[PDB]
Length: 139
Image (cartoon, rainbow, N blue to C red):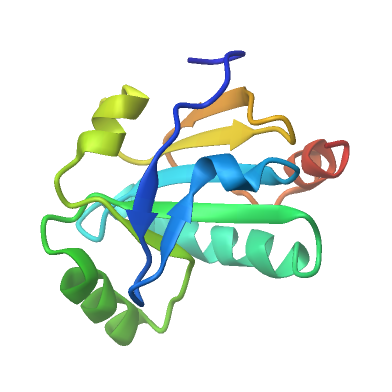
């Protein structure tokens, strides 16, 4: 998967909208696969929100794909109790995770301006840290 262009997909947002990875050429993209019931997923959310704020106004899009069987209702609940928020896409049936060849969660893909997959990261990271931020700016 790594070093070859990202497989396309179209999915619903929390609010009836739809996002198609191809129309995002020109921007750097992070596709992250996560779930409300995954303790590592929840460990790294705070650090993923700080990566999002740092990028506001820049040609950058973060896509947090949820695999919760409970969808919008499950993610909405989780966000109500924790106070967290992120740019979520829904994938309850797990087919885009399968398309992406994932094995468990969290798993994160880093995609360049030409739509090519540059990096695959397994497990909770600290997305707020300098090397990552500066790896992204380079792009």
